[PDB]
Image (tube, rainbow, N blue to C red):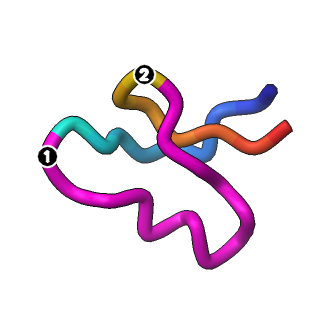
């Protein structure tokens, strides 16, 4: 539910490394 400070319009969430995921073009975790 909290933003990881990264977007994923065209690239992946490199913050997936800390458990984030792409949710409607913005990287979030919990």
- Residue 24 higher or lower than 14, as above or below: above
- Please report the residue visible at 35 percent of the width from the left and 29 percent of the height from the top: 25
- Residue 30 vs residue 15: left or right? right
Which portion, as a residue range, is magenta? Answer: 10-23
Query: Which SS class for mark 2?
Result: loop
Q: Position of residue 24 (x, y in %)?
A: 42, 22
Q: Residue at x 52, y 41 (%)?
A: 27
User: The N terminus is located in which quarter?
Assistant: top right
Establish if 5 lies above or below 14. Answer: above
State the separation of the CA atoms marked 1 and 2. 12 Å
Q: Is residue 3 above or below residue 24?
A: below
Crowd around label 2: few <14 · some 14–19 · many ≥20 (10 Å): few
Q: Residue furthest bottom?
A: 17
User: Crowding at label 1, few (<14), some or many (≥20) Cα neighbours within 10 Å?
Assistant: few
Picture mark count: 2
Mark 1 secondary-structure assignment: loop
Q: Is residue 19 magenta?
A: yes
The quadrant of the image that shows the C terminus is top right
Q: Position of residue 28 (x, y in %)?
A: 64, 38
Depicted 29 relative to depicted 14: above or below: above
Give the mark nearer the N terminus: 1 vs 2: 1
The numbered disc on residue 30 is none
Residue topped by disc 2: 24
Give the farthest residue toward the left: 10
Q: Are marks 1 and 2 in contact (CB under 8 Å)?
A: no
Residue at label 1?
10
Q: Position of residue 6 (x, y in %)?
A: 42, 46
């Amino acid at each position: 539910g909290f933003p990881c400070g990264e977007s994923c319009v065209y690239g992946p969430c490199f913050t997936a490394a800390i458990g984030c995921s792409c949710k409607s073009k913005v990287c979030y975790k919990n």
